[PDB]
Image 1 (cartoon, each protein chain N blue to C red):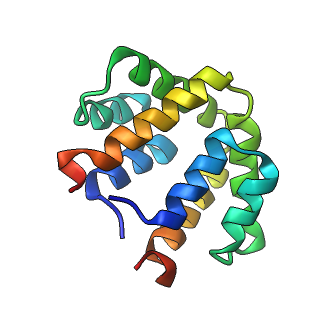
Image 2: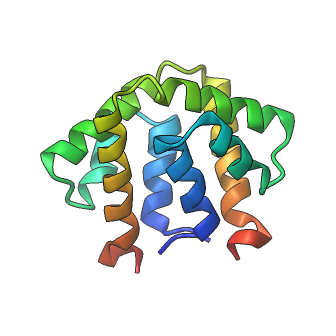
Length: 70
Length: 70
């Protein structure tokens, strides 16, 4: 379906704090550039309403649990 | 590593047009709400510089190809 650590990453991206996202990322030993790019992503996603991020999470689960991703 | 269709989705999200992202999504038969949420995501990611999106893509590949996602 989906790499468990990756899912954690996405969960923290959409619904968690920059803090927890940050910890999540460090597992993968990103370089400073990739880490910076990822925080730029977080900052902008955080502009979206809560409801919107919940629906993106729900959307993400529907993709990863599709017959198409089996 | 990663569901091939999902990866396509992400690729189109970060580096493609709203158009191609849109086609990509439809595979998964998203409802109108999930589709709307996903387009709201696209619109905001599109605010980020090209370079930034390239690095997020590179970051994404590093995650999916980690020993941790084996």
